[PDB]
Amino acid sequence: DKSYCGFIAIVGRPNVGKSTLLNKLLGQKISITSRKAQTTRHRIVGIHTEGAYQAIYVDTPGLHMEEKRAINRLMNKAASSSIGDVELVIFVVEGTRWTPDDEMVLNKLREGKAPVILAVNKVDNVQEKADLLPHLQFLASQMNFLDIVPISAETGLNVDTIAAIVRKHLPEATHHFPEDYITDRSQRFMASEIIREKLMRFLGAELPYSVTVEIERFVSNERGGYDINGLILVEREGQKKMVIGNKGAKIKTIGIEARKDMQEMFEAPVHLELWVKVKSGWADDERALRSL
Amino acid sequence: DKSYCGFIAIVGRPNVGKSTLLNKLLGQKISITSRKAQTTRHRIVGIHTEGAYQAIYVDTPGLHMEEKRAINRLMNKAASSSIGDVELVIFVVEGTRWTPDDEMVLNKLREGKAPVILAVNKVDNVQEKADLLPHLQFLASQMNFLDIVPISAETGLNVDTIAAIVRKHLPEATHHFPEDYITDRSQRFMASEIIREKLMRFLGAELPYSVTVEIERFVSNERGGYDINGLILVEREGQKKMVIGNKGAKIKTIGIEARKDMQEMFEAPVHLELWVKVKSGWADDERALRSLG
């Protein structure tokens, strides 16, 4: 009978695992991690809808009036239509690291009426726990966190835990967005989206969890046309062989079919270059082929 | 800062002026009056958005849960997403007429939490007011109407007044719908929509502040294809002469362009038959041109 919907923040200095945490929270089988300097004007970074709950994830602790009108334009709603406020904040930090950049973010939060969760990422990396406890005690000394939760974004350590608090903070309200609305309407996202389907379609029963599509390059040329470079990141090594398939079949197909739509959708032929890769890093041979 | 949005009803027995009153409220220059005896599952009949206010006009006094689930689907929202309730009701009646149908509607209303405005339509068409006063006093005995207001079907007598009470009844809330959302996603509406553009594109606003498009026919054949019949309705006579244009050029163009998008925007071919008409009834020649095919 009742539904809940609200905005939630995910802040932290760059390269802390924010994007990885977001994808785990969005709960999509095949995710789409973009690398944009092109900061949205609405700051929406993803929307998780499930049952009566709709959490709208933003990358700002507080939503400006400017950001409120932009969210409305995104929804094609009157600029005057009411938009709430951030109800929770997930402050992500990296293990035992603490730069003036981490403080910069922390400084912007404390000065708010929104509760904040400290998400300590890559906590397993710190092989010297003798660094951890002292650190965590120093962190908690920075402000009153609603909670301090250590996570592994690539394992989903305490993502369910953060998922639960997040929902507890969704105010009673009607959803602002239709279920599968797109906040990224760029061609670059359209591209990632076509690859995503081809993987889902062609991998079939062999699709593993945690796959991530991403456009490393989308451009035109001095000779004209659309140069698109797809990056299909996977968790394991053997998984990488799946996406590639027998003789290179599966990755061949996914690429022709994906290129097809990229052309049917966009209005220009595209030279699509699809690269499978394990998130832990390229391999020797791969690093070689990546230079050819 | 604040914003308001809520559902409002427009009830009444058929052929009373509900559709005309609605278009007047929607405030659109060129309106699109359907005739869909096919009743929606969401019951949305139109949405008036302006500034922070968004009134969602339905054709049911009260929204059933089923009618709520359908509204969400229309918006492509989770079935669970909250939908409010009818905050006001416009019960339109025809002049001095009162059938068991008028009563049927009024009975459903009597029992409800929704304030209801009595809209007396075609009031200027009553043969003798000596029928009106006794009637009204008898209507106002049926229940406590928030207000009793007489309106003119095509003049928009007190449409502003009904508009102003309607907005007063919009609860504080966020707009459920994007500004220009379409509640009718049928091809029949897509057609009406194309003629609207062509009128707006070619008439160039020289246009009658009250034109009304309408698909009088949209079908297939025993021989196959798409038989579409457009009905462009205007107020005055010269207006009709405007839409037709010199040598019949304007109406010729509006139809080739309209037929085109209907050709493309739909997958197959269309036999578009566009007919201009004054709402006050056809003419002799026209009736002659119509009475054949």
Image (tube, coloured by chain):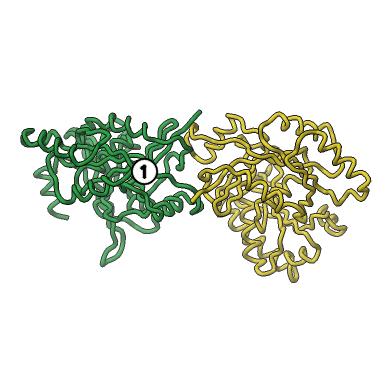
Chain colours: A yellow, B green
Foreground pick, B86 / B272? B86
Q: From this view, report whether residue B41 is shown above or below residue B20.
A: below
Q: Quadrant of residue A39?
A: top right
Q: Residues within 10 Å of mark 1 (few under 14, many from 20)?
A: many
Three-letter code for the amino acid on which mark 1 is drawn:
Val
Q: Nearer the viewer, residue B96 or A288?
A: B96
User: So how many labels did they put on this image?
Assistant: 1
Which percent across, then down, holds residue B205? 31, 31
Q: Residue at x 67, y 60 (%)?
A: A255
Residue located farthest toward the bottom when viewing the structure as drawn: A246
Q: Position of residue B133 (x, y in %)?
A: 11, 33
Residue at the image point whose x is 78% and y is 31% from the top = A104
B272 horizontally vs A134: left or right: left
* Residue B237 location, quadrant: top left
Chain under disc 1 = B
Q: Which residue is mark 1?
A: B86
Q: Name the secondary structure under disc 1.
A: strand
B70 sits left or right of A6 in the view: left
Is residue B250 visible in the rendered structure shown here? no
Query: In this rendering, would B224 be left or right of A279?
Result: left
Rendered-image quadrant of the C terminus of chain A: bottom right
- Name the side, left or right, on which B247 lies relative to B71: left
The x and y percentages for residue A92 are 76, 42
Please tell me which residue lies in front, A145 or A177. Answer: A145
Position of residue A160 measured from the top left corner of the image (x, y, whole percent): 70, 53
